[PDB]
Image 1 (cartoon, rainbow, N blue to C red):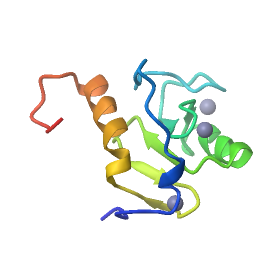
Image 2: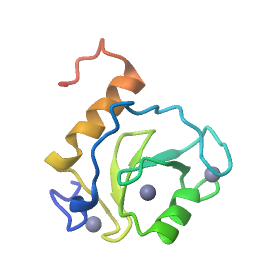
Image 3: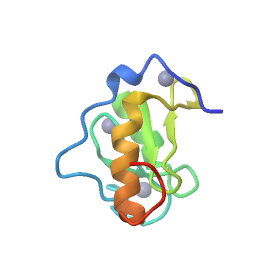
Image 4: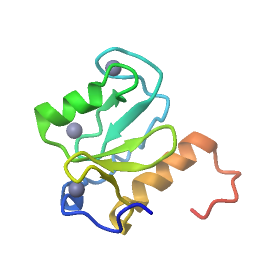
Length: 108
Ligand SMILES: [Zn+2]
Ligand SMILES: [Zn+2]
Ligand SMILES: [Zn+2]
């Protein structure tokens, strides 16, 4: 149902060894709600339903792909579609572990 590939996956960068914090607030407004993490630079900003700071970040950086801290979906702002691919497996997994803990039935 998401796209199996997009031309912007090349811009997905290595996950920091620091890992991900799915409860990290928006870097601009500080909201705890509807945050996304940028898969290029790993700054965290809010979704369109709050103050739209991730969309603003896309506009001012050109960074393509972002991961939702709500449902762990990856969205590309250029393709205007959700994407799932091997390049996104590391981040989605580390995010899932941080969000739900290790005691989960989901394949890591
Ligand atoms: Zn915000
Ligand atoms: Zn970015
Ligand atoms: Zn794309």
